[PDB]
Structures are given as C-alpha cells and as structure tokens.
Image (cartoon, grey):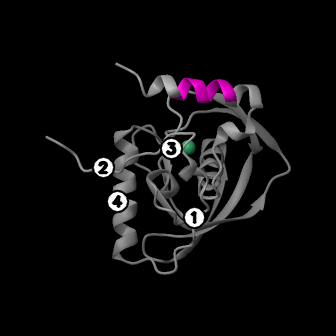
Amino acid sequence: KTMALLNILHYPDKRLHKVAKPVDKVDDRIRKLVADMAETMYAAPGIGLAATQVDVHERVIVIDVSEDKNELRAFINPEIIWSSDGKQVYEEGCLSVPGIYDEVERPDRVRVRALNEQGETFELDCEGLLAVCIQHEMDHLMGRVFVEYLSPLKQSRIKTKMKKLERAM
Ligand SMILES: [Zn+2]
C-alpha cells in the first residue's frame, strides 16, 4: 500500500535557502500542512521538520523529540523572544542531508512564542534536545542548513557525499 507523503528536499538544492513567509491565517489548509508534515516526519523517520524542507515556504514547523512519538508540537510563525548567553554543542543530523552528522554550537536555552494549530498564541521555554531542535527547524525557515555552520572544507566534502547519495543502488 502506497502512502501520500511530502517530498523532502536534499542539500544542496537551492530551494532550501528560500526565506519562508509568515502564515497570516491558520486555516484548514495550514492544519493539513501540519498533518502532512507530521506524517512525513514520522515516516522519514525524524524528530522535526520545517515546511521549507518540503518546498512550502511558509513559517510552519513540527517537532516530536519524544522516544514514544507521543509529544508532537506544531509551531506557526515561531519567534525566539529570548536566548541564553550559555551555549551547548550537539551533534546534529538533518532530514535534508541524509547520512551526515556534525557538531553545531547553539544557545542552550530559548523561549519561543508561536501560534498553534488553532491560531492561539503560546510561549514555550526550550532546553536540551528541544532547544536544539527548535533552533535547527527555525534556521530552515530562514534558508539555513546546519552544514553552513561547518568549515568550507566540510561543506565541500558533504556536497560530494550528496552526489553519491543520488546514485545509491
Ligand atoms: Zn534539518
């Protein structure tokens, strides 16, 4: 049985650098995008996804960092309203860069304001893995892939790996 999923763009596709526009109205269309994005993320599988990655250039993110896959959260027009001076290093992968993992330094805590699937405004203190994931996904909406924080040498080697990835048997 086939499954209707959204295609995930791969680095270094130029469309991953497009800046997403804000969601003006959280309508039934946006709730469907949240639904299709969550299905696409769980099937990949992965723990977050930005609409940019499926070639939908609007400020929509879904995240589920839980092991049981029982903590799905949607973030529409997210805003970092406070960031910590403290930084932590974490080895990130990315659904748009399959097979590539490297350390990234980010603020270790952020507070985000966003809209939920019902257009209500909410605020969330993020720490640990969630703090990494939300910043990773929000980077995607600004056209940023995590490999852009790596050295040019490493970006060049990743680009070569991505060409291998397309020729896999
Ligand atoms: Zn990613």
Instruction: Please tell me whether residue 166 is drawn above or below residue 126 in the rendered image.
Output: above
- Is there CB contact under 8 Å for labels 3 and 4? no
Magenta stretch: give its range.
156-162
Work out how far the residue at label 1 is from the one at label 3, CA to CA, in angstroms. 23 Å
Q: Which residue is denoted by mark 4 in the rendering?
A: 35
Amino acid at dot 4: Ala
Label of residue 5 in the image: 2
User: Residue at horizontal 55%, vertical 65%?
Assistant: 59
Compare residues 123 and 74 and report the one nearer the observer. Answer: 74
Q: Which mark is first along the chain, 4 or 3?
A: 4
Amino acid at dot 2: Leu
The secondary structure that dominates the magenta segment is helix
Q: Which mark is first along the chain, 4 or 2?
A: 2
Q: Which residue is denoted by mark 1 in the rendering?
A: 20
Q: Which residue is denoted by mark 3 in the rendering?
A: 65
- Is there CB contact under 8 Å for labels 2 and 4? no
Work out how far the residue at label 3 is from the one at label 4, CA to CA, in angstroms. 17 Å
Left or right, 35 with reference to 93: left
Q: Quarter-wise, where is residue 108 in the image?
A: top right
Instruction: Please tell me whether residue 124 is drawn above or below residue 119 in the rendered image.
Output: above
Label of residue 85 in the image: none
Question: At which x and y percent is residue 136?
Answer: 63, 47
Q: Quadrant of the C terminus?
A: top left
- Toward the bottom, the furthest residue is 25
Label 3: which secondary element: loop
